Image (cartoon, rainbow, N blue to C red; front, side, top):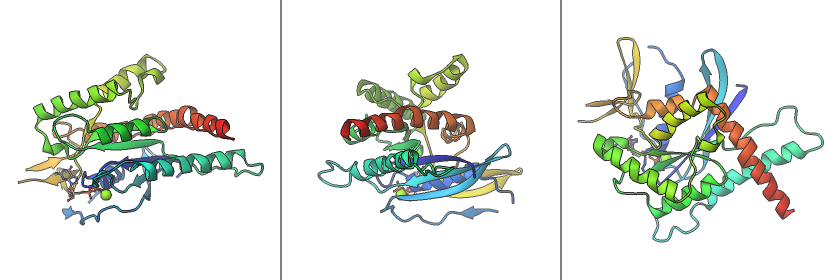
Length: 272
Ligand SMILES: Nc1nc2c(ncn2[C@@H]2O[C@H](COP(=O)(O)OP(=O)(O)O)[C@@H](O)[C@H]2O)c(=O)[nH]1
Ligand SMILES: [Mg+2]
């Protein structure tokens, strides 16, 4: 409840974004003791913030996940990024104003979007122009971690090849994703960040039910077998989960404050 971290999920509707939010919170909020299914989630039509307290080791922190409406459902989707871009810049503006005030708060509320999870449809080809355009715009103002939505849609071979095509599109379009190579501070950071970089975009699966096996809580998605979403042999959600821990959260925030928010300040100076 001290250290704050804000994640936004972004992507077209029907990619399992709202589902993965619930999966992520459950993956970091321990629960001992029954076989239960999840309720159906309505289509997300408004930007909404979901905040829960989570504990790592024994230290508490406030995790906020921002759910967003879909884009790309229309014939013409020009400027469909504006509501999300507006939200992001609004948080920067709030923080800036709190910071510049003469009688500022002793503890400034940080509602800045520290990272965006960008959901890519599991098409099997390459990145769509819309998603390229949206991620490009986002990457200029916020940390981006792309993910393959509903990765259970892909065989392993399809997944490997799809990742190569997506990475090629990101790189050829100059879309920097977290962790950016230029921000590696030392050799240990490099070795850790290389593994993340090689795995991005993460093949994730969202859970629709939980149970317990041999004392261990399993977050799972049903199929005509059960996908254990935290099993690294089933999908890569666990790697995403592990990226979103105390130490890397801090590095993500550090880039948000020192790179993106600082860039925003410069923008506000070049305007007035
Ligand atoms: N196959 C598959 N379906 C999923 C996954 N995650 C969610 N779903 C289903 O996809 C549908 C849309 O989920 P939702 O979270 O509302 O997607 P959103 O519109 O992006 O927020 C729901 O019926 C979910 O049960 C997944 O990882 N794989
Ligand atoms: Mg949704």
